[PDB]
Image: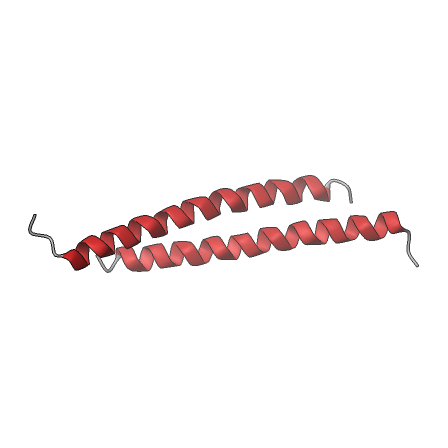
Length: 41
Length: 42
């Protein structure tokens, strides 16, 4: 029953933060993979 | 010239992994700037 404006704002910010977190982890995983494989050269 | 195929494969793999990392770094940076801009509305 909260104002649609606030509801939409909170959702959009939450979603952007989640995207950032996901990509942070994806990047960390890719770095770990590259580093592992480099030390197997 | 004296490198085995397996090592050529490993080099190609590392090169591809470094590129995946580079692209994800850019993507993450873009997500971060996006989140910063969105959080201004709070």
